[PDB]
Structure formats: C-alpha cells, structure tokens
Length: 127
Ligand SMILES: CCNC(=O)C[C@@H]1N=C(c2ccc(Cl)cc2)c2cc(OC)ccc2-n2c(C)nnc21
Image (cartoon, rainbow, N blue to C red):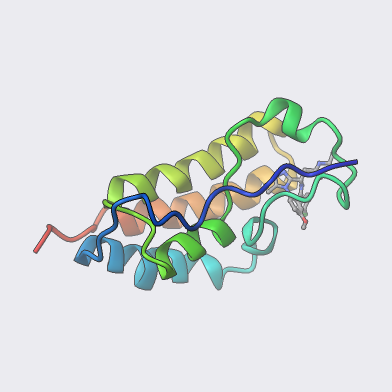
C-alpha cells in the first residue's frame, strides 16, 4: 500500500501575505477546531496504509486536512482568507464523499463544520 505525497505546505514561488483575516483563521478558526474532541482524525493527512483504505486516494483526488492547513497558516502559505476557507471546505467535502451517511466520522466532520461556520460567520473585515 502507498500514500500519495502530502499537499504542498511550502512554495517560495507562491506569493504570500499575513493579513488580519488569515490571523483570525489561525488564532480563532484553526485553534477552535484543533482542540475539539473530534479533531484527531483530521489533524494529519489520511493514512490509507495504516487505516487499510486502499481505495481512498482512488476516490479522493484533492486531499486536505487540518495538519496541512495548520502548516499553511503557520508558514504564511496563503495570499487570502478564501484559499484557507476552501481548504477547510475541501476537507469536509472529502469526508462526506468517501464515507457513508451517519458514519461516526461524518458526525465528527459535521460537529467541526458547525463550529467552522460559526467562526467564519464573524470573519473580520480586512484592515
Ligand atoms: C470503512 C472505514 N472507513 C474509514 O476508516 C474512513 C476514515 N475514518 C476515520 C474514523 C475516525 C473516527 C471514527 Cl470514530 C471512525 C472512523 C478516520 C480515522 C483516522 O485515524 C487516524 C484518520 C482518518 C479518518 N477518516 C477521515 C478524516 N475521513 N475518512 C476517514
């Protein structure tokens, strides 16, 4: 069994910013989800080898996780908040696409997504 390379978290060619919205995405949004009891399956890329999911990366072609998002935020990988918000939404969508309705993992994603939406609802205006 083989995992793909992880998503990119570093690229000197990619233009970067440190904005108040991106700071909020780290300090409020990422931190709130990371500390949650249901955070652990989402704190690193899906390990298809260890989890015995040989079809995971056959079905999921745009992998994303909070480990990657955390690295992207801490290393100022993004230009804007929209990029980061998309990463969170890709993470949730992947979970819903791969898994069955009512699965424990789907309920975990839903609880995290509820908090995500609550926090992004009060994304600050750009300074
Ligand atoms: C048929 C079995 N299905 C799975 O294992 C899917 C897997 N399901 C889980 C998972 C996590 C928690 C529970 Cl209670 C049940 C399943 C999961 C657990 C992990 O442990 C390190 C990593 C990624 C996960 N994950 C994510 C994220 N999206 N799908 C899955």
